[PDB]
Amino acid sequence: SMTSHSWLCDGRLLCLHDPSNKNNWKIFRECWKQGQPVLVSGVHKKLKSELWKPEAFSQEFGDQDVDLVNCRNCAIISDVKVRDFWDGFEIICKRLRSEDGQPMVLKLKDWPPGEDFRDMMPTRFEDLMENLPLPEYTKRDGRLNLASRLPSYFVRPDLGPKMYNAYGLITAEDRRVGTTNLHLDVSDAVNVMVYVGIPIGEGAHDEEVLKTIDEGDADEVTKERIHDHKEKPGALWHIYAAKDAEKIRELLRKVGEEQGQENPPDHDPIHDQSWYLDQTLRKRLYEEYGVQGWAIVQFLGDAVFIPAGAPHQVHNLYSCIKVAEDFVSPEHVKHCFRLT
Ligand SMILES: Nc1ccccc1Nc1ccccn1
Ligand SMILES: [Cl-]
Ligand SMILES: [Cl-]
Ligand SMILES: [Cl-]
Ligand SMILES: [Cl-]
Ligand SMILES: [Mn+2]
């Protein structure tokens, strides 16, 4: 039976089922006021699927110059053509190779660059912005988006959206690396999975993906979305409450010191964007500091709502295209104020 919502993370995460329902705010706003993330499924069914394919991005934009990041070691690959990234998205035998001769796991850095998404891709911009869930919060002019209404005493988000494109992490060693390291934003964000690419050439890679989700602490209902409904999983997220950010900074100062980093006692390991919390570090955070997070698997068409101030990290299971929009809800406006 079609239902308004369900729960993940053993009751700790709201999952809304219908992305465009005018009644969603009534369920959403109580969870949001408490500083919880929220998942909305089914956004892919609202979009024009032909606009969100890796082959179309290569054909239309392939001659642009870009930088890539090697996710395994954080090395920058400078001034290559964007087709060198897109043509290897799903076909492993076409990927740029490291010196060891392996195909690299790559992230496309800042593309489209800065605020240029709308100018470069006007049909994509329209398709995304018209189908975002919770539109009074997420649209540039929504009644509960304060972004366009605040004075300079508040940090205002840039004009979006922003596109986040990266290969899937593959090996047992890759389980300890992030696609995007632990960081926080002073604005709220909605992040939509518009495409998941399951590769070929080393296709048969299904078992390291299950072990990553299991060791990632994903709940039993999340696991049933794969085995029972055959949905395509894109990325594993860990999100922490804004109120736990300083305890996470204390853990990462102690670990920085154990590993022989030499940091001033006030330095900010979350702002540095240099850490990925692996199974060892997540268990340490829980046992030693009393901090629990939310382990979230984002499937094709899932929109993840990330509260302002909430530390979070992302680990791609397969090749992903994500599009995100920042906004300023009244619930969380304290996080972007420049005083006290
Ligand atoms: N998605 C949703 C959200 C809030 C309120 C109602 C719905 N819709 C619905 C449709 C059939 C049966 C029961 N609920
Ligand atoms: Cl808050
Ligand atoms: Cl376009
Ligand atoms: Cl709304
Ligand atoms: Cl990062
Ligand atoms: Mn972020």
Image (cartoon, grey):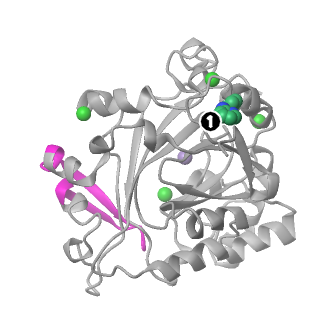
User: Which quarter of the figure has residue 28?
Assistant: top right
Q: Position of residue 322 (x, y in %)?
A: 43, 48
User: Which quarter of the figure has residue 308?
Assistant: top right
Q: Position of residue 24 (x, y in %)?
A: 67, 29
Q: Which residue position is annotated with label 1?
A: 186
In front: 171, or 207? Answer: 207
Q: Is residue 246 above or below residue 192?
A: below
Q: Position of residue 264 (x, y in %)?
A: 68, 59
Residue 88 visible in the picture: yes
Residue drawn where x is 35% and y is 79% of the image = 203
In front: 304, or 25? Answer: 25
In front: 338, or 2? Answer: 2
Residue drawn where x is 80% and y is 45% of the image = 243
Residue drawn where x is 52% and y is 43% of the image = 42
Query: Magenta part of the protein: which range?
Result: 60-83
Q: Is residue 265 above or below residue 40?
A: below
Residue drawn where x is 50% and y is 31% of the image = 132
Q: Amino acid under label 1?
A: Val
Q: Is residue 16 above or below residue 209?
A: above
Q: Secondary structure at mark 1?
A: loop
Neighbor class of circle 1 (other Cα within 10 Å; few <14, some 14-19, many 20+) is: many
As for residue 74 lying within the magenta part, the answer is yes
In front: 158, or 18? Answer: 18
Q: Quadrant of the C terminus?
A: top right
Q: Is residue 232 left or right of residue 241?
A: left
